[PDB]
Amino acid sequence: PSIKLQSSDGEIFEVDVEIAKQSVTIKTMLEPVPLPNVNAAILKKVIQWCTHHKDDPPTDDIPVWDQEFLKVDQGTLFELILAANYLDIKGLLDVTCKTVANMIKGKTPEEIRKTFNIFTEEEEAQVRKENQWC
Amino acid sequence: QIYYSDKYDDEEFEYRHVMLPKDIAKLVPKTHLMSESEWRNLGVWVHYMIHEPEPHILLFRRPL
Amino acid sequence: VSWDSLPDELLLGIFSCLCLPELLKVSGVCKRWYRLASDESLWQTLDLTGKNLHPDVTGRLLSQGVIAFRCPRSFMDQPFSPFRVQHMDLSNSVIEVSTLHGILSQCSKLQNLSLEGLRLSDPIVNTLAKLNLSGSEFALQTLLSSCSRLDELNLSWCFDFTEKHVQVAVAHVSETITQLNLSGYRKNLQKSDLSTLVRRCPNLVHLDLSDSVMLKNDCFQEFFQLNYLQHLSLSRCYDIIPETLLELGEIPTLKTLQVFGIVPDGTLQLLKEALPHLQINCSHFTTIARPTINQEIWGIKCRLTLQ
Amino acid sequence: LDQIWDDLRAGIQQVYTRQSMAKSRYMELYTHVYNYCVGLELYKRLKEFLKNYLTNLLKDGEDLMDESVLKFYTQQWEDYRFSSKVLNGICAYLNRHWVRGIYEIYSLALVTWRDCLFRPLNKQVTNAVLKLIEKERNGETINTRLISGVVQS
Amino acid sequence: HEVVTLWYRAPEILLGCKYYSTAVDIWAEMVTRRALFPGDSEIDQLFRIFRTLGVVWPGVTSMPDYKPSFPKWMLHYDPNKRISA
């Protein structure tokens, strides 16, 4: 059957039961509603990922497609992870968490802090002293 | 085969280096050291450890 | 694009897929990240073999919610709340006797630790008894009954065992023992002890009972009582019937061919004729109460492995 | 914001009463679920509200002893279970997700019903159920859901 | 790193440090002209030196063949402190 949903801006999108089976927060819905948190851009992005990734058994040990799929600016990734946490998804949440973990692998503290856009000179000496064991 | 070495040490302990044929080296595992009754195929106490860079070294222990 | 507005357990998802270099790297950015570094969920399995650190660092680590630990061949010599350590074995790293207060004195509950070849004093066993001990007798006797649920007890090559110390072997009260391995006291073990030891334990799936020299006539068939303890484990025997060892195992069920050892030439190859139904022994190696087996043993894979 | 709960409590309160409702209420409260996070002092307020509502409901349960208390008790229990199910299905994220009465909404409702049932009303409910059973066994038959509800409870 | 010679093996190679600078030149392969020289196996060659000649080596516990359970008993032991020819 065909199920429609209401976007925050006021758009209407078509969803299918098979395309939304992997979800749990909208599966209960399928079993139009206002969703201000999500927008049209993420709706098409999530729905296209679900269509191309729907049937599966129950580099970097991740699909090669995801490398070019997630190559977006930091702002969109912030919106994607916020939606994933709200939608309590598993497949998308694990992929983006792994991608973030790989991108924070072996990086200088100055570039990590600047990119993240977020305790120095009083405790840096102490933490350095008891972390040379590694 | 059995190898012999001088049982001399600076401290009160005593150790001797031993070697085994390459054919019997397959049985010896690098994970867990051998025991007293384990090493009976050679026909020659307990296997303490091995060498760091070398793959074949036996010392054995002697109790008072 | 502020990344500090997320909940802590979404951050735990990011931290669940990191190794020690980056994990200790990311600690020094902010107080929040500093606290989320040390959650019990992240530190589950931690394994450092031979990194020669002092026990203050590993005490800091036992203060950070770890559940499993496997560290052989390290150097910890120089000298808290009870902690949740179910899975921690040991291969003999050189460790100072005095500095066991910071390691073992805190925790005595749970599945407990497994030593081998470690020389230590009585009070440590006294706190432990509130479990391999390879390499006083009252503490050992108390610890034997301390863990009634545990069935596997291992001890071999004791350097302070007297003739009277072997008398407590039959005094061990345990009706649920499944596997055991005691040997090496050929000149100290009493042949009459095994007759009562067999009766005491209702069954014993594994029982080496090697290093027998006298080989008393009663012991030839006294041990063989039930069908749950059938085995042919024997080694380092001087006086024994050659090529006629099948008399002890009149009704064997499992495949056991642990008969290698000091035997005269010409009899090892002829021993196969005494057990045509069974196969020939291929390899001999003890696999009982092994601290580790090449690291996925007991389902503990160290995501925080240094290598 | 703590000031949102005092105005939004009516949405949960009207769930106990069976009538029509607006479809947007589900999303309205679901947004406030995570919008609350401050973000920890909610369990105590919910427990206090549930306890006071349950005491108020039990207060009007004395004038009925037999053939009338059974229907009333069954329908109030059904309403309470329906409200608990709605509450569990509408907010089940900021309860025990972070680290850890039981924190679960369904378990909290069950334990509150269990420790509130110890009041002397249990004896009168049991007496009514027994007398209904004997009356049924005398030869006549009547409806069964009245005590089936408390049995399933 | 690999050395075919036995009696004149580079000390850095035996210690597990593959990379070394002018270590061979600083370390008379056969001056005794007899059998008293320590000609032994890969580990026994270092064991003989340890037995013969017993802070001294800063940063010693950072090599593949630098174990912590070892016993206590122009030739320069320190690789960094080596004088060129």
Image (spheres, helix red, strand yellow):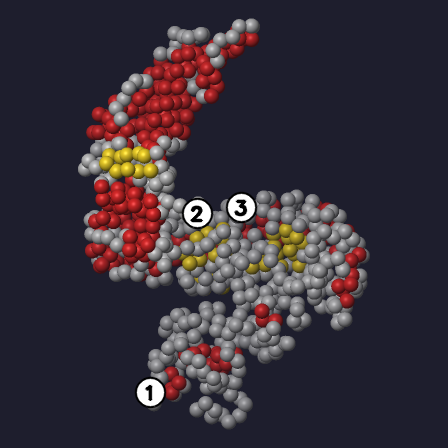
> Which labelled disc corresponds to residue C130?
3
What residue is drawn where x is 48% and y is 19%?
A: D151
Q: How dense is the environment of label 2, judged by Cα within 10 Å: few (below 14), some, or many (20 and up)?
A: few
Apparent side of residue C64 relative to residue C282 in the rendered image (left or right): left
For the point 28% across and 34% down, which residue is it? A4
SS state under label 3: loop
Q: Identify the subunit bearing mark 1.
A: E
Task: Identify whether C259 is placed above or below E60.
Answer: above
Query: Image check: E63 left or right of C233?
Result: left
The residue singled out by tag 2 in the image is A57
Residue kind at label 3, given as amino acid type: Lys
Residue A89: give x, y in percent of width and height. Answer: 34, 42
Badge 2 marks a residue whose secondary structure is loop
Q: Chain of mark 2?
A: A
Q: Nearer the viewer, residue D136 or D131?
A: D136
Instruction: Locate residue A117 relative to residue D116 in the image: left or right.
Output: left
Q: Residue at x 47, y 11 (%)?
A: D143
Task: Determine which quarter of the picture holds residue A18.
Answer: top left
C-alpha distance separating marks 2 and 1 = 65 Å
Residue C197 in view here: no
Foreground residue among D24 and D112: D24
Q: Quadrant of residue C75?
A: bottom left
Tell me which chain the residue with mark 3 is part of.
C
Location of residue E48 with respect to C218 vertically, above or below? below
Q: Which of the two marks, 1 or 3, is nearer to us in this view?
A: 1
| Residue labelled with disc 1 | E84
Q: Residue C37: horizontal and vertical position, in percent? A: 33, 51
Q: Nearer the viewer, residue A71 or C205?
A: A71
**C24 to the left or right of C238:** left
